[PDB]
Amino acid sequence: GVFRVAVSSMISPLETMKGYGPVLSYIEQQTGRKVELVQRRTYREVNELIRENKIDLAFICTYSFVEAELFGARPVAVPQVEGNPYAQAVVITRRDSGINSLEELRNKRFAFTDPMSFSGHIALRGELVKVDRTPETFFASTFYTYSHDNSLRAVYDGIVDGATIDSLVFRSSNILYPEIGAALQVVHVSPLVGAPPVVVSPGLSEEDYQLIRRAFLNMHNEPLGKQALDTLFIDRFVMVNSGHYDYIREIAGKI
């Protein structure tokens, strides 16, 4: 039977099959099953494919993982990038805005990515619980761009006063677009959390689960595996530590 791998189409528009092609070939090599890439615009739609066992494996985000384990999604492995399997949200404003803290964004225009993103949404919804607020009752207006890059573009262009995005997206964008880099600043950082895990649908056999986990954990020792990792700009995949996601589980409960 076909092995279906799901991803968000909004992380690398037009370059998704370019990025994942070699890791899909790696999965073909290790499983002997033909692999189909399944794309959806939103992490909610990807989670619905997992819940209804319409796919085998998904590259999901850290917050969608907390919702996904509740309907039996099983973590396989975590990407190790820049020598660590962790992630962090940054809140960004224009240097020339005079908005130098999360606090000063009260009654201002703000950009989120996907509603199911930690670094693009929930990290900030979580922190606002401290002051008995939501984005809706804290900011003058909010927008969901479904894109870390588009959220950064909106801050740069003065469409919004601030955004929450992934720290690695910000650092990478600062190198690739230095005029945009020069104009922005980080005014707040989230806690460290675990990076987005790779999951399998609740309907897989124990043996298929073990085979896939071994393939991911050993990917950096395999010739086609190394091509897959280089294409995704990942060092290797490492074991999931559930405790790395406990801050997100706690935020999620406070809603």
Image: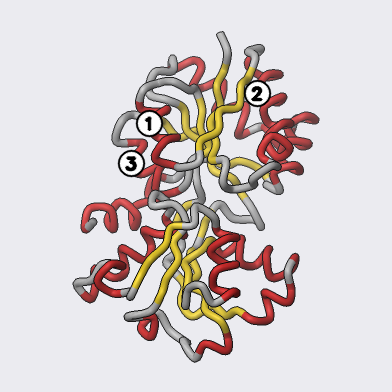
Q: CA distance from mark 3 to mark 2?
A: 25 Å
Label 3 sits on what residue type? Answer: Glu
Secondary structure of the residue carrying tag 3 is helix
Q: CA distance from mark 1 to mark 3?
A: 11 Å
Q: How is the image coloured?
A: secondary structure
| Residue furthest out toward the top | 1
Q: CA distance from mark 2 to mark 1?
A: 23 Å
Say left or right for 116 vs 92.
left
Above or below, 159 relative to 30: below
Q: Earlier in the sequence, mark 3 or mark 2?
A: 2
Label 2 sits on what residue type? Answer: Ile
Per the rendering, the mark at residue 67 is 3
Say left or right for 9 vs 181.
left
Front position among marks 1 and 3: 1
Q: Which residue is mark 1?
A: 48
Residue 189 percent across, percent down from the top left? 47, 72
Q: Which residue is mark 2?
A: 27
Secondary structure of the residue carrying tag 2 is helix
Q: Quadrant of the C terminus?
A: bottom left
Q: Quadrant of the N terminus?
A: top right
- Tell which of 72 and 92 is nearer to you: 92
Label 1 sits on what residue type? Answer: Glu
